[PDB]
Amino acid sequence: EIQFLRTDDEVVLQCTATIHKEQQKLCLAAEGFGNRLCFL
Amino acid sequence: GGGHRTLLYGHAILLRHSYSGMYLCCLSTSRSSTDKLAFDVGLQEDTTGEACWWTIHPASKQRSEGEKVRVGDDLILVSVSSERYLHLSYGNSSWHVDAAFQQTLWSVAPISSGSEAAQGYLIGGDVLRLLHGHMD
Amino acid sequence: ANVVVRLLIRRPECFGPALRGEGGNGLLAAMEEAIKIAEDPSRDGPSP
Amino acid sequence: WGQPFRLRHVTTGKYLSLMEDKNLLLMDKEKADVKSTAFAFRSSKEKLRKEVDGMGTSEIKYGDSICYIQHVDTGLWLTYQAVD
Image 1 (cartoon, rainbow over the protein chains, first blue to last red):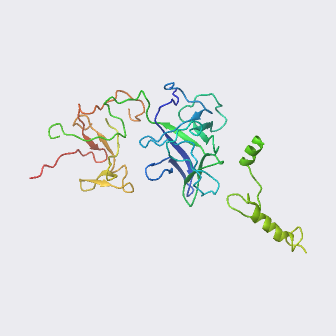
Image 2: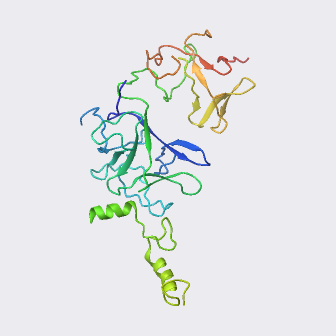
């Protein structure tokens, strides 16, 4: 029933922010081939 | 290294974008001026010792340092060099991740693990090429 | 000085008349506006 | 078996669908949805956990066994229209 985050485990990141008065939950994203930045 | 060691709050963390091996880490990112004083630490493979690490801090006062990070725990991230948190700004009527002193909550989730290995078995997200047994 | 600047950066509230991000956090614009207040008026803006 | 997913054509970057006229077409992300782009495997040709969180005997092995797609919304089955 208990499990932690180890080294070398595949994770995805998430956040919750309001927009248009609606809690738009998102995930971090990035495509480092032509743009080294990050998007959601 | 250690090998499947656990994860503690406050310890230095290293990330990696999976298919594009660009180690998101402490880089001299001074390009984003949506907030006009804020960084956007993005993707580049420069794992260089001190300028290699973000750091965890807990979301709120329920789990102190030295405790093991558990699934579902929302967290707070920060560089060591710039010491900006992982900010979720709003540049122009839209979302813009930046790095600032206004922190942001950043929830993690499970996808798989080392024990969750294929060895030929199917795993979600994996590409493939379909085949007919007769017609190929 | 370390902990000082650490605490300042969480809440750096030297808010002058008008600049980006904060109110001020920039000296020349606020100083020139306060010099418009200073020279031809009194300490106050509307005063003789 | 019995997990809805949506097939993405990787090169064009368009999601597989099944239009109203019963013919497979790809679909851009803005058009895709769980009504059309939602497909699951079928071990046997017959019809007949739900919250797939516990693992429970990992099923599909590449190369050896075989599958059958099911558009779970329509329940149709894939078939190669051998044309003359």
